[PDB]
Length: 182
Image (cartoon, rainbow, N blue to C red):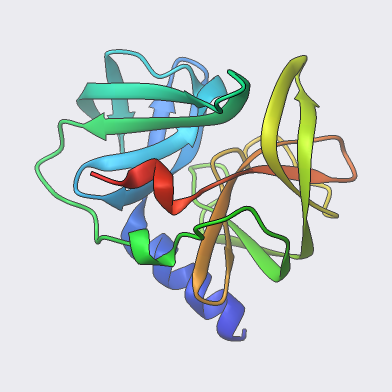
């Protein structure tokens, strides 16, 4: 409807796939080459389904900060025959707060879904399903089961992936440029 949704749509149409693990279907953001991200609670194994195609996982790393605290991001390298458009220049370099964000989801359950979530707070620490977690972004939207892996954007920036909620608020793990240096 406006330039927020325009940037979100541009990322969804070229840089997302549907990932299926034994723990469900997730929006999965492709970042560059055959490298993508997914919430760590998806429990990626040796094989994953990508748009319903059986795909070998070449590498998977659950990220933690230098306090050895969970970040809830898993970086996955996929044995896929095609590269993603490189979107690393849209990733923030530092932790920050944001205005006027969009959460975008694409699964079998929620195709072509875009949610204007509004102001995003650098929340920091969250006990997420019992697991101490750092670098959490918070927005005041009642997000639901099925939105995990959803991409959080502002105009010009890809800032996080949705990892949970409490029924009133939603929470995303930060994406930082430093996670994807090669």
